[PDB]
Image (cartoon, rainbow, N blue to C red; front, side, top):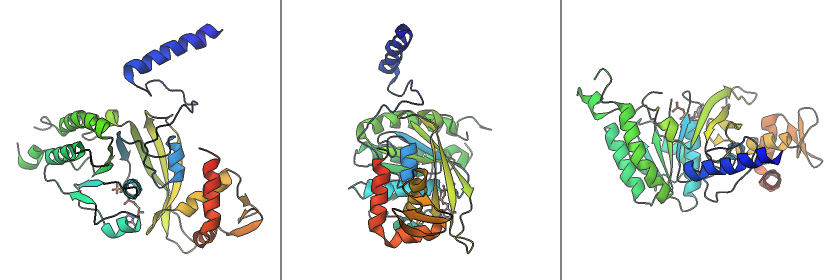
Length: 310
Ligand SMILES: Nc1ncnc2c1ncn2[C@H]1C[C@H](O)[C@@H](COP(=O)(O)OP(=O)(O)OP(=O)(O)O)O1
């Protein structure tokens, strides 16, 4: 009887000593703790990730439909890793970034590095050496797909001299660097030229806009769902949902009203949210309005919501 479970252990462990940690996991295991971790400014996602945020020194991929949220996450990530004496670098090859939105998200623009490569090759070289300086915490590439080769942009084919070669290369040599430097790297998507990225990424996130969050009126943002389809640091397949308000981004408040009930610290006495006797208000975003101004109560709720997990 114990020979099986014990033979599986000697073996299992054997697998880690040859191929790393998360080589063989078990969807249940809570096995743990890597101090280094950048909170995504989404308590929700953070636990779904298992280790409470994006691992540092690992390459990451956030993919999905347009306008779902991927970059809003990445930018929150920046802001966190940044508000802790972190130095971020945003290699922009889409010319889409909006500093006024980034600021409201807590990002330090003035101190944010911004490269606007010309060739895909350039971007990955600049990113590479820039990560080798071991000075950066996080680095994000906006749009994997928009990293076209020097050739495709000139004339010199029919697919052969590839992008999904340019990707395998840079990814190969840059993967190591990150390990040492302990810099964690976010890549945005929408394979294409990937097929190599999907393998490297120690964590892959499948983002998608589920609901169209309205505040009675009609528009305020939208509900985003995220499935962590690959995780070599914790158990995969967990998922999370959070609110994104056209203006502020991931709703901290909302993120609590959700967790607050999914964990009983708040009661649904019929569309009427309540916490320890006193009422928060009727209507999901009416309670967020309560949790907004009353930070004391939220601090305790967040505090209790955090103690109930880890
Ligand atoms: N500058 C902005 N001001 C206000 N809301 C914004 C802004 N940028 C994005 N949003 C809001 C509106 C959208 O419903 C939502 C989409 O987030 P966003 O981070 O742009 O997703 P994304 O970058 O993952 O997707 P994409 O693949 O199209 O690049 O966020």
